[PDB]
Length: 281
Image 1 (tube, rainbow, N blue to C red):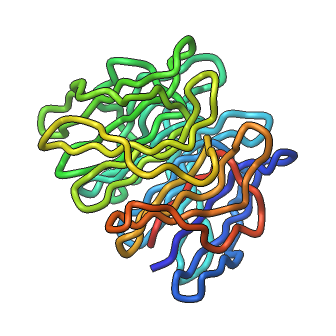
Image 2 (tube, rainbow, N blue to C red):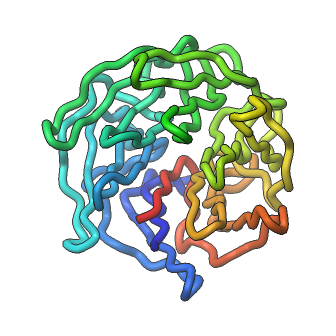
């Protein structure tokens, strides 16, 4: 019942701090810091732990992974990725965490690795058809979707879906707008692609994917343009946390109510954060 904002970049420093949002109090509070500063970090939740995967510490692209236990309020290192990855998308499906794409400092990645907590190890799985850093990843009805990103030359509107039973990625409907640094979350059978950057403009637009129709449709726009935004879903609302509007790194947070199809501002973060990972536990 808390949203965690993990790491990021405030415009001057890559962050190891972590803040947690309680919707009942509408406030953010600091919790235990990461061992390593991480922007462009992927974050996901599995079996009561939050995993902070990869990122960039200001000097090095990271292969390390840390796990947060809320009962102990501490982060511990777990198995490292095979490949350093910042701008990596992370999602959880059927007891595995998937690290999708990213950038290793030299190359934009099409590779994908899966973490099994029982074995505490990462294994490579099927690669994406297109290299993607700054990719948004979400899970819906047994498929993992890799949304947008940047392949080193082009900001992407394409979207691919992974079926673990087939261990393969297949293209699905493209976004209306190219988006890297896009936040993605799932609510009530739709995938939302929030903000991002199209190569020329930081975006306030938001699009929603219906798998039954295999199409994206525009929904209400954010009040503030946000790339490098973290997105998570809690109790029927989607939260867009931080990001960068082209001029300023943001501490603001907005919440989307699908019944009203509108975004409203909620409590701000204590620290401006773009390239922030967000998860709910």
